[PDB]
Image 1 (spheres, rainbow, N blue to C red):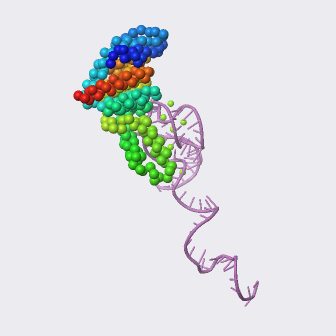
Image 2: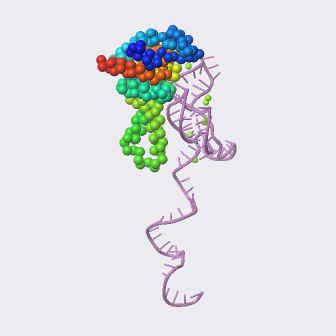
Image 3: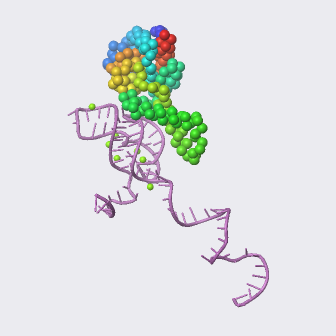
Length: 224
RNA sequence: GGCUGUCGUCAGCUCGUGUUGUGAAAUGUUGGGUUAAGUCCCGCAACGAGCGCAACCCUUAUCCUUUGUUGCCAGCGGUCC
Ligand SMILES: [Mg+2]
Ligand SMILES: [Mg+2]
Ligand SMILES: [Mg+2]
Ligand SMILES: [Mg+2]
Ligand SMILES: [Mg+2]
Ligand SMILES: [Mg+2]
Ligand SMILES: [Mg+2]
């Protein structure tokens, strides 16, 4: 990753001056047109060492999950995870899915049974009414937790989009002592994240840049 | 003990795990619509489940098939009708 490629995607952009969190005053260079400018000369070493640690953990054989739930950012997250042989969540984060795994992991078995009944020819016999409920059940259990169906246990790292919009997952992971790599704007709380990567996180270009970089480094680490 | 009346055939009453609070407790069960209904859809630090609601039970209203006595008489023969 290079500084010019970062500035080309709008990473320099931040948020307004009246919405800034003073916990990351150090990661701000200046302000123009009543908008903060992120000191990206801090961003480059952070991003590089974060990628190094991510691919090291990939070589350490630790499954990972990609967390992004924005309405205009789901496809990038799901594709970056899918073409990485890893896991993803792109809808509402079902609260407690980590700390309360014992009661959500059977929703996985329910989804699997429903999908076998779907693509096995079972949805023909019954009296043409409950198939509607079954189809909606497939739809909802696919949208909610259909991206971790083959998770098979707790993860070993988490990648987070919009630390503000995704703080419940951050607390859930912090409970379990699992490292978190998150993207933070200038209105974010960097307390729960041990590997902090500053940068704009409302533009599609920067988000897909980060996702491509992390997918590439994870494939590198698996190539070991 | 067993059995019964009533609020009231009113739509309510709880639990496991998770989270919040020093704590009694809270969330779930709140919010927008909608229904006879905690009935259903959407959103949601909650995810699921149980007793209730509804369905399964009896009878009535339409048609179909089988059997015709002690029940019936449309088409034929006789009549004490
Ligand atoms: Mg406590
Ligand atoms: Mg109640
Ligand atoms: Mg309550
Ligand atoms: Mg409430
Ligand atoms: Mg309501
Ligand atoms: Mg109910
Ligand atoms: Mg009933």
